[PDB]
Image (cartoon, rainbow over all chains, first blue to last red):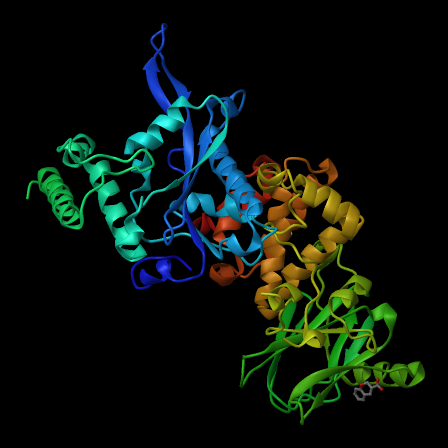
Length: 237
Length: 300
Ligand SMILES: O=C(O)C1=Cc2ccccc2OC1
């Protein structure tokens, strides 16, 4: 079935599961041609595949060369996403392979199910959760490695840094979704909240700043405030 | 002209023979159906007046033997039986007709409908789908499930239709995932026509049989199979030209014959919109398109 919030804690039980977001796979810049027309140029993209319990992010970088000479690219991108997710699953030891893959966009269901035919016991599901993984490229270090790639490349990250030393997976996912929702809503202001104090640094091997427990509380309330402020501006409340 | 005698008609019933139907009252002096244009195939079916649950019936070839109907008050249904003693059967059939006790198979000469519907339907293939080797005729009813349904619970009572599953290894070559899902030509031509059905006539025969089982019995798994075998052709970019042209004629007569008030339950909106308006073969079903629009515009 589909996921949501009746069974939102199940995301953090001990059946391995992966979220797959494909919204940054095919990425273009839209510009105007010499004859007046409008033309696209592709830039590198990525598949966002996340274990919500562990924080392990499998960031498969999609190099623009994969689109060369192909047609119907937005359709092809779903199939390319499915091909790489299946390849990732096949490269993992059996005891590490997911029992469920949850796609953030329902258009991915058929492509992934067809590429996953060898794994009949792996459930492929959509979700009714609105997740902000499209904003993954607002995380500077993820954007940098995608834009610098000259060839297809897989990069592994822990998107929770060291948070699980101190909080639960449920709390870390909620912090992550809050952060990304704020970056999706008002990116420049969200980045300012995070970087406002230069004495709080990002460790070389982390994505986010090394906040203390009390600072994360303050940061989380500023992100809530940001999202709520933008809601009011949008709907004149 | 063959004859189907009925021992008695103890319960009020609607009797179908091929595409026709008539009513019989409880304990009405009804002894059968005469003047049946011999075929290659035929179907006699029943729906009891006091319980229209379970429609059931029997596919049969008059040339394979002499068949009659005898009501069984224990199982509570009209059962088909075979009479191996030809002389006895002649004796009953050359007499009860003489009495005036049966009704005539009412074929109009201009009417080639039943054979346009059953052109590729054969009894030997029917008996492979409905497995009951000791009988030369084949029982089907409203409730029977297909082997495919059973895999998603009594195999003896199953409809052994050819399993068609678009999201299965049989349909999708490794390495050709997108290609074969978007263009089912491999699955149609290599797997189904060359591998399993051998020729397009057998393919069309199962399609016709499935349609008729859905229409006459309201058998849901049969309707699924009918729509799947249509969709497989329409979703293939490469289909032999003789198949395409014949498909338009097959479907046209099926749509032509469908009860007008049964369209909400025998037609799958998704499959038909895809085949007529979106698929590779949209422009190959001209007459089916024309009848479906003029007859069922509400589905599309
Ligand atoms: O031997 C037979 O085949 C029959 C016997 C019989 C008797 C009276 C009416 C119908 C019958 O059906 C046929």
